[PDB]
Length: 256
Length: 292
Ligand SMILES: CC(C)c1[nH]nc2c(NCc3ccccc3-c3ccccc3)nc(SC3CCNCC3)nc12
Figure (cartoon, chains in turn yellow, purple):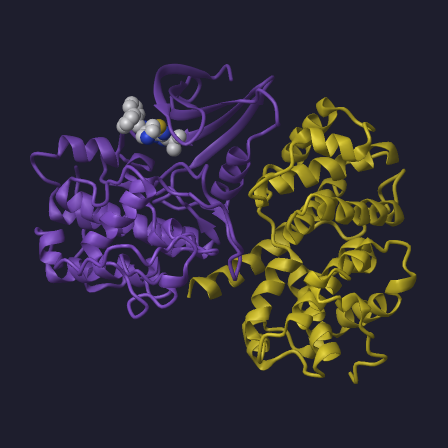
């Protein structure tokens, strides 16, 4: 009964920890493409440092919110991404990587001084509000509603969940809770032909119908994934850990 | 930091120095938590405490009032309380804490903890030294430095969390997973410590702490706690003590207090009582807010 209470709190909070949808148009010197390169790198950084997937989902939330309010020139975009990932590791990790290793993986592009100082600025700009809801926090809850649990479905919905991180357009216009429903349903329909279950229509208030806009963007992403310029998520999701589900065939249609 | 006048150094808790200070313009009395930075940046203790307490506004949870960064200093500005539950129990060692105040204090703690849990926060260091009292008969959870935002369902988090005496058995046995029951265990321990004014399980090693628990509640078996005997740090060599009768464990305590404490110290974490359910227990039918 503290479970239903958390779902409710997260649904309130995911609206307040939301970035401004078209913030990238107001960024004079950076673009969605530059962002999607930085996010794909942070995946590679997650893997080397064996960071949690949540650490990555939080770092992106921090990056997007920071860029919603601060102009960043391209030569500084990797420093925002580095500082956010260090902040997210400090919050979510048992063993956060030390600063001098975040420096190493930038290849001395930036000093310790600069990483530490951007962490202070990032904290300032996010007003220390780092306990943000993520797609993965909704996914893990959705997974308790499987009939029955299926490790191919879990890893596929996670995989799909990560693909949304890369592409600000059109995912930034969807709430984490909604992306995580799209992801869950699409992974389920892909692996078992089953759909968004009743138990979650009650829990979430989300009809299969209401998920349709996001689920059609996420279908496309899924389809066009092997051709996308960012490929670190497909590499990561080949390891046996994730039941190599990035090797599976997207469905052609959803019968929607 | 020019608006605050230091009055005295209060002490040190889970991290940093704490000062009593006065706001020179408003007169307000605060507790300042100083954190020095040297050279990994802002400690994860501070990052978690600040971010979580900003989402934990409750009358039974101490208030974060401001965060200040000056050169190589971080000050968290907090509501002040003149007393902790430990020193209050030391003063009351000979006398006793009046039963209705034991009840008020436990009630309040469960209200504060239920709010934490429903906001996906584990405290993970509940003990009398982190629970603060004022003169109006109010008690409050403090020091969220060792707290954490948890998920549904929980991942594996840090092992050897919680001060030994207040640490739940599923931690000592090295369960991969722990959640909110850990916090209920601690308040179980603190409930009985209010009743008897001595610590229930004062171990000096992890094995001694376990053996104190087993001596009192009985060595658990695959019936009491399904899974226990194949947990990482379970040894089948452990002595089998039978369960001591609670009227001996907490002599002062009525049938309703005993029922609650029992359910707060359930071995199996899945059957151990939640804060919300504990608040609804008959022991709290007749509860008031008396004064120390
Ligand atoms: C940081 C925020 C949450 C806060 N608000 N009030 C606090 C407070 N008041 C208590 C006090 C005041 C004035 C003189 C003495 C004491 C006092 C000192 C020791 C024991 C008992 C009482 N203390 C503490 S620090 C802690 C040290 C380790 N554990 C116990 C208290 N933080 C406070």
